[PDB]
Image 1 (cartoon, protein in one colour):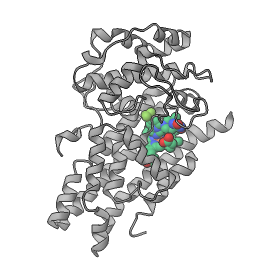
Image 2: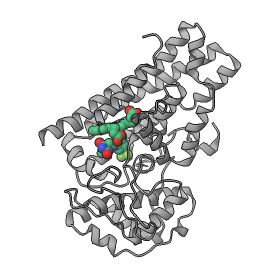
Image 3: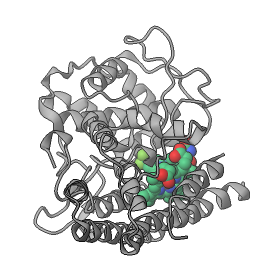
Image 4: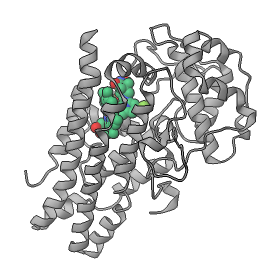
Amino acid sequence: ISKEYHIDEEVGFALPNPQENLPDFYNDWMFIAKHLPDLIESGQLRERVEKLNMLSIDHLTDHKSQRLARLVLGCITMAYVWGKGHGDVRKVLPRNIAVPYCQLSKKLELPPILVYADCVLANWKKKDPNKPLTYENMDVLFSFRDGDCSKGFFLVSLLVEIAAASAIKVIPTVFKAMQMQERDTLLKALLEIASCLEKALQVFHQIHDHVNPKAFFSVLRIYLSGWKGNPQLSDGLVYEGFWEDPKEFAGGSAGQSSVFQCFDVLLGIQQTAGGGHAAQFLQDMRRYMPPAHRNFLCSLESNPSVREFVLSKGDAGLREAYDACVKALVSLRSYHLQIVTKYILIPASQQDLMNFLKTVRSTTEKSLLKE
Ligand code: HEM
Ligand SMILES: CC1(C)CN(c2cc(C(F)(F)F)cc3cncn23)CC[C@]12NC(=O)NC2=O
């Protein structure tokens, strides 16, 4: 795989070894982000941010320092807008944060809001740089509240992404085998993709250990929400010294994950095609991906479909290997569909989402050939 797509051999679409510290110039930004649970609980967060100074982003050289600052500013922004998470919101992002945020967001071709590539792909570190990438050897860089289970939610999401990312290096073999007409090579490549997607489901099971439902629903769910289609910020958020009027940006979501949209595109599931509402939502989230990953999803679409190759040829061994990749995705979205009921549907009852997810699950399951 070419380098300008920013695909790592080990962590896939995740940022390889994200740096943890900013330069001393931005030490004031760092203090608010590193002590978010304490400043919010104390009720001194919103005025600590208001007393900040205007810091120019010109001293944030290279990619990793910009991705960390975007993670820092994104977390601060979520804490300022939502506050303690009880309904008292702020509709104006002060200039001392709003100006360099959009200014830096323009340099990375990302919207000025905390996205999936921030709080998951760049929000981690190896506790021991010598040991493998296990949950016991990692930790998040920033969290919102005490006991919000953000470390479990983010690290498990990262580990599912890394597990599913080991099948990305197989994608070049799939397209080379098609143009060379190598049935045996294409056969083995598809089986390898399904094997990596089945390991991703096994990693998904870790989430029951590190995330409890009530903490996710009543705490962490608040700070991961955006201001697009949100009644609490009806017309969006004001970015002060950058925009003349409000702006509506969607909150973080795994619809912004390039891995799950890669294999939907590779397998011809065409989750973007259809013109429906769920198809438009996933095409929208592509704008929330880093530009190199946005370009990678688009390059796969320029190739002949893997689905039309297997479909035309009467090869039962090729159809079962293709369906093994499709079935692995259905197994993910089905177990994920149980996850939503445990941490959203059940906690909400004790106090459109469902319709969107099983619309994606239905489109995937209707892409099978044998069943
Ligand atoms: C931790 C590993 C997780 C992974 C790998 C994951 C994966 C995904 C993906 C790929 C999507 C886009 C739709 C589709 O392609 O399926 C999605 C959307 C969604 N997920 Fe997750 N998810 C995870 C955790 C969770 C948890 C813990 C919850 C609730 C407790 C949840 C609730 C939702 C909802 C309500 C949507 C659709 C609404 C929207 O995306 O804003 N997910 N997830
Ligand atoms: C639950 C949540 C509050 C957050 N969501 C989310 C966020 C992230 C992320 F970026 F933070 F890492 C990853 C992820 C995977 N699956 C769902 N994810 C989407 C759905 C959500 N957002 C909303 O607006 N309603 C909702 O239920």
